[PDB]
Length: 352
Ligand SMILES: O=C(O)[C@H]1O[C@H](O[C@@H]2[C@H](O)[C@@H](O)[C@@H](O[C@@H]3[C@H](O)[C@@H](O)[C@@H](O[C@@H]4[C@H](O)[C@@H](O)[C@@H](O)O[C@@H]4C(=O)O)O[C@@H]3C(=O)O)O[C@@H]2C(=O)O)[C@H](O)[C@@H](O)[C@H]1O
Ligand SMILES: [Ca+2]
Ligand SMILES: [Ca+2]
Ligand SMILES: [Ca+2]
Ligand SMILES: [Ca+2]
Image 1: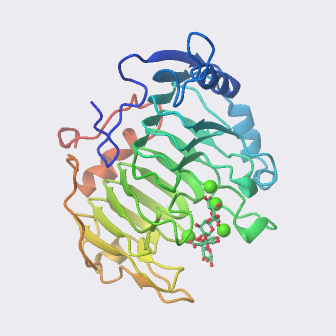
Image 2: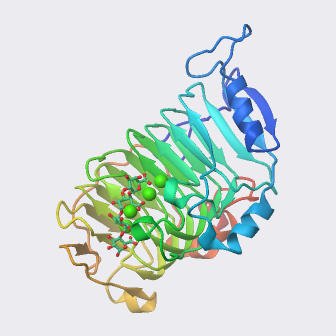
C-alpha cells in the first residue's frame, strides 16, 4: 500500500520490478543511483531504469561527533548531499539500524521517493544549502522515521547571520504532496521550509507524529497551500512554531506543545496572514498557556499570534485516512516511535 498517513501516497522503491542494493557509504549510494539509470545496454533510461530500494549501512559517527565538537567550523565547509534528481521509477533510501550520515539527501524533480531510518546530523555547509533533507519540485515524497539533528545555535559571522546550519527538511517548489512523519528532529535552528520565497506558495504537506525538541523555528515556515499537522510533540521551541504565511491554511490537530514560544503564528511578512483550525491539542484555551509554558512575543512587522487559541479560518476536508491518538498519548508514547531504530513502528490508539 501507499498509505503514508498524509498527502503523499507512495511506496517508494518497494514496488513491483524493484531492485535492492546495499550502500556502505555515500559514494556507494551515488554510484548505485547512477547505475540504476542504465538499461541492459548501458544506455540511460529517463526517470531511472527500474524501481530501487537502497539499504544504507554506512556510519559516519566520527564525522558527526567531530562536527558537534566544533559547530562553528561547519558553515564554511563544502555541503555534502546525495542528490535524487529526475528519478521517478520509485526509490527508497532506508538506513540500517546503527547507520548514520554526515551528508544529506537532496530530492529534486523526482517523485515516489521515501527516506526512512536515516540518522543525519551536524551537516557542513550551512552557508551553501547543506540540508539534511531537501524536497524540491518533488510530489509524493515520504520522509519518515529519521533522526535529523545539529545544535540549535547561531555562531557569529555567518552569511545572513543564520547559516550556522541549514535545514532538517526543506520543501520547496512543486513538491505538491509530501508527508513528513515520525522524525526526531532536535537541536535544529531552521527546521524546514514549505516554500522558499514569498512567491513559492502552494503544496499539500502533512506533518505527523514528529518529535521536535530544542528547535528554533520553521515547523514549518508555510507559504500558501495546505498543512495538516497532527500528533506531533513540540517541546522547547525557542523562536516560533508553525508559521502560516502567504494565505496558507493549516489544520493543527491533536499535538502537544510545551515550553514553546510563538507555537502557532503568522509573522515576518507583515501581510497575507494564513489561517489555522485548532482542535484536540493539549492546549485548548489561553488559560493552558501557563500550564504548558507557552509564551508569545511580537514582531516589528504586522503579525498574528494564536494567543486567543481559536481557529482563524477553515480547512478543507482531509483527503486521506488517518486516526490520531490523543495529545496525551503523544506526550506519553511518541518518543518511543519517532526517529531511528524503532523499526518504523507507528503509534495507534491501542498502544496508548
Ligand atoms: O531553500 C532554502 O534553503 C532557502 O533559504 C533561504 O530562505 C529561507 C526563508 O525562505 C527566507 O524567508 C529567509 O528567512 C528569514 C530570515 O532570513 C531568517 O534568518 C529568519 O529570520 C527570522 C526573523 O525574520 C529575523 O528578524 C530574526 O528574528 O530571526 C528569525 C528566525 O526565524 O530566526 O526567518 C525569516 C523568515 O522566516 O522569513 O531565509 C531563510 C533561510 O533559510 O535563511 C533563502 O533566502 C532562499 O533563497 C532559499 O535558499
Ligand atoms: Ca535549504
Ligand atoms: Ca536567510
Ligand atoms: Ca536556507
Ligand atoms: Ca523563520
